[PDB]
Length: 435
Ligand SMILES: CC1(C)OC(=O)c2cc(Br)c(O)cc2O1
Image (cartoon, rainbow, N blue to C red; front, side):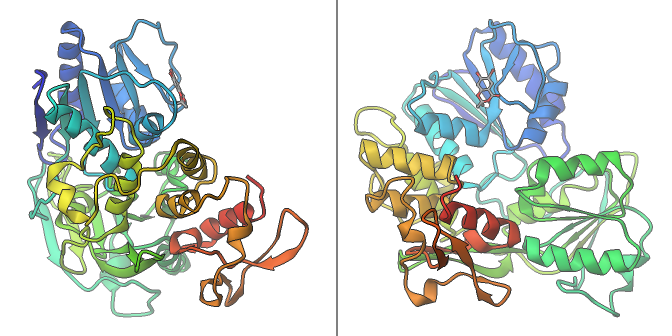
């Protein structure tokens, strides 16, 4: 696996031991061969689980999620998928790793797709080896893979709103349930309905993941209501998964705006990962998987693959060459390699709008390519009337950095800046010049 010019896909079924059993063996072999190695974790929670599996091995943990006193002689680095891509983009020297290991390599966030593109190109060039660890590689058509113990799979109508009757099976259950919803707002309504019925509910989403995930260990719960973030190695002690089989899809319209389309069917990879949360204990057969719709290839035309191209066009590889997306996911976007390449100063603005501004990739690109500087927020207020952002059925308003009350009306509308109360609050702070 570790020899140059080779990319290996380690596709053992969910719960087969890729992280706890296979990963330490690969690391020992890499250290024995003096291979400068990088291990890429999707989240800070997975990074913490990896430190437990690799305890006693000389690994440099480039994350504050782990508290370790490094020796300074480690040749193995561990960091998140987003940190790797961020460091490549910035004027920071990233070693050219001989071995690149990506855990939960199915992650479809733009920074993860970009990391796969960069690593696979280095391998194609004959410069590095790579191991992608996932039960569901890109393009998988099997939503029902093998598991540690048998699962009861049931196609059933799943509520997506509060209900009064017709879904007794949901609340009549006495075990623990992990329920995947298409959005934070949809999970809020189902959570409220379950709480009113006497259930103890925890909610998880990208922004709250590390903090709220700890509650799944620290307190008794009946339900976990989660978005698709829990498809990336988050493990639970549960006996049932309820899966709406739906997700939101960011779509770029006429290259001028981003909408959150759907809810629409999840990919087979996502469904297999959601189901994969249960059937993990070989001594507990009969875990349930209730699913409320079919699968479709909704990653085709999904904005994340276009956003991965914007990131890869701005990463130095060799002279004017640009890394391609990983071959099995390369047809998900129609893009000219190099079309998003920015000049030095615009690239710096693009990076800062993402890193400090916390803006979606697409939106950060529109601002930086228009020649606007990071602190210039006039674009948050000079868009067309149809770009007015609404809050509680009335236009959102902020005090500008000049002390003037203005309606939020960005020149470029990206629905992810107001997909929920938390996102809109963060965007309002940005428009006001507060970060
Ligand atoms: C990832 C980030 C920003 O934060 C860390 O926790 C960290 C730790 C080490 Br060690 C390192 O070399 C670099 C790092 O930079």
